[PDB]
Length: 6
Image 1 (cartoon, rainbow, N blue to C red):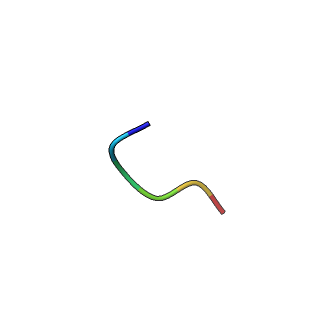
Image 2 (cartoon, rainbow, N blue to C red):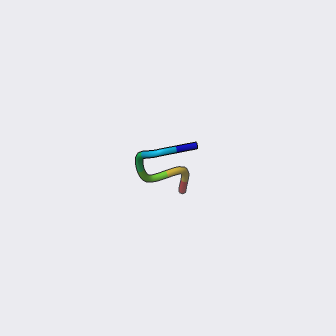
């Protein structure tokens, strides 16, 4: 993961 996980 390099992004946003909500």
